Image (cartoon, rainbow, N blue to C red):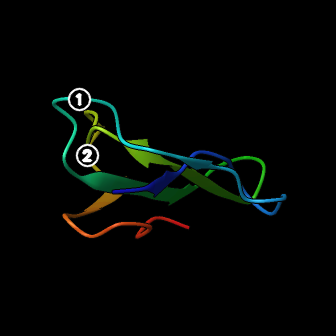
């Protein structure tokens, strides 16, 4: 499987999900900079208001 590991707009770099991690996660939410988009494997925790779309499909978090 695979999961993007960058932020905002930049030469997207891919990281092969590590053991245990079998899903990708996309954390998107606007802040004081504009549009912040975190991404990677291992659906982390978030705060009420931020969106986290997890998908058990390779490359699913831009």
Q: Is residue 44 above or below residue 36?
A: above
Q: Is residue 51 above or below residue 21?
A: below
- SS for callout 1: loop
- SS for callout 2: loop
Q: Position of residue 50 (x, y in %)?
A: 37, 53
Q: Report whether 54 appears left or right of 41.
A: left
Name which residue lies at 25% across and 42% down.
Answer: 43
Residue, disc 2: 48
Quadrant holding the C terminus: bottom right
What is the residue that sits farthest to the right in this orientation? 10
> Which of the marked residues, 2 or 1, is nearer the chain's N terminus?
1
Mark 2–mark 1 Cα distance, whole angstroms, equals 28 Å
In the foreground, 45 or 61:
61
Name which residue lies at 26% across and 70% down.
Answer: 57
Name which residue lies at 41% across and 58% down.
Answer: 26
Alpha-carbon neighbours of circle 2 within 10 Å: few (<14), some, or many (≥20)? few
Residue, disc 1: 19
Q: Position of residue 61 (x, y in %)?
A: 46, 64
């Amino acid at each position: 499987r695979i999961c993007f590991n960058h932020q905002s707009s930049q030469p997207q770099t891919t990281k092969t999900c590590s053991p245990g991690e079998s899903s990708c996660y996309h954390k998107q939410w606007s802040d004081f900079r504009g549009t912040i988009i975190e991404r990677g494997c291992g659906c982390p925790t978030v705060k009420p208001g931020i969106k986290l779309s997890c998908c058990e499909s390779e490359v699913c978090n831009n």
